[PDB]
Image (cartoon, rainbow over all chains, first blue to last red; front, top):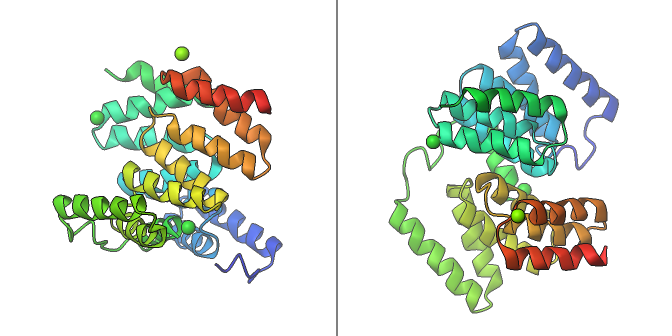
Length: 128
Length: 142
Ligand SMILES: [Cl-]
Ligand SMILES: [Cl-]
Ligand SMILES: [Mg+2]
């Protein structure tokens, strides 16, 4: 990868990541998408870069595309259940409530992030 | 590897072979069986190609991912194995076998606290009593 060869300096990469989120926070989604795609080309193995791109797909209602990337993000992180939470949201939008339930249940059972667990439980409470 | 392919596919967001149903389910089953035929006979290099082929076609298949992860673990490519085991768990969230194997990989990667976390999860959440015994044996050694 480009990261493996140190093709752009670390501080420049940080800046691009911040600009990507600046675009995202301002609702400049097309530009944010370009920037997160750029970041994920540069380092496919970076969980936060992958999470930024998955968030763009989720915003654009490309819920399967987002869920796929979230699954990769979880795997690379190991112990961050934030991607699993967002996968749950995607599964609800895909009309797969039992898959969604499974995601939120995993957050509740495995995560030590108390605020994330509250959010997961709020979704579980709503699922019929 | 199989993860970079999945990510490149997601980035490019174009038509994949899966999107067009380029290989039918029964053909994929046959290739999977041939992959394991190679594996069972110790032809690991050919098995690896076949599981890589399967994971290019349909990366989000627990059984395909598990086959490939096992090969990397045998080859002492422990980071690669751990990553794929974590994918396997994510896709099949009720089977703690991949979490157990991730624990093993983490110990070999000199990450005992990550390993401990994996084996603890097995103990707390798995209903596989024999797997729990194995997980506890590793916890006792940490
Ligand atoms: Cl469902
Ligand atoms: Cl890879
Ligand atoms: Mg129990």
